[PDB]
Image (tube, rainbow, N blue to C red; front, side):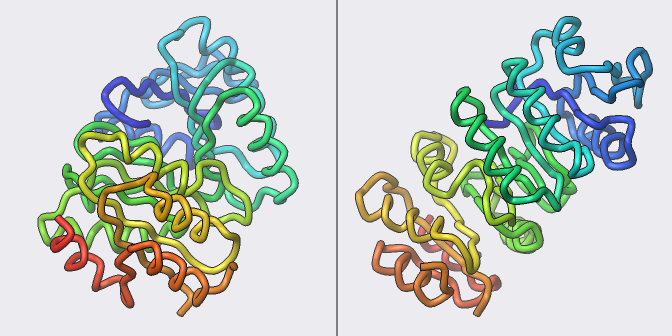
Length: 269
């Protein structure tokens, strides 16, 4: 979902986080072509042109295909609707603290319109060496063949870094969010990675709550994902126990500790 063709629009760019990450993404090599902040149109942040609306940004920059949201919770839902209605197909929502019902509403709307939501309450996505649409520091990642999908932001960093230190690079790393309801799920992520030629193995980082991990083991058991899967579930249906048992009966190598993931991956490779 994230590569050299990524053209990013940053919603909430004049803000503290929006401006900082717009700069960090640029320095990493991500093509950030514009930003939006109502009332700041005509301005500029770190060289990036600012527009009062997504519509105006797109008029002047039609190559935009991805948006990242750094807008406070009260305004995050609106930012998502504005992007989707403008035709943007991938919207990364970093924003934390959005009422669950509101997220349920804009995620369903996005699904209805053919848009993909990553988040909310997530660090975004990164394809080491190609592009970053998120908040993760690029130095802890490395270009490789292991996909990482995670509900936990901290574990995404810790586990990715561990893999990198062992010389085990990643294809695309996606933090799908830690809220009760998020957009892209483990099963959907697995579907994407199954068709990704750069991905040889996948690391699934879950935790208690929801049935997303259980549905992923379910789709794997059905043979919908045939590459090796190493998982880790924090919190040691919805229970830690139930998730582990479920993934294991699906043929997934579950790690007892995060420190065990690298070796589980090295062998599977």
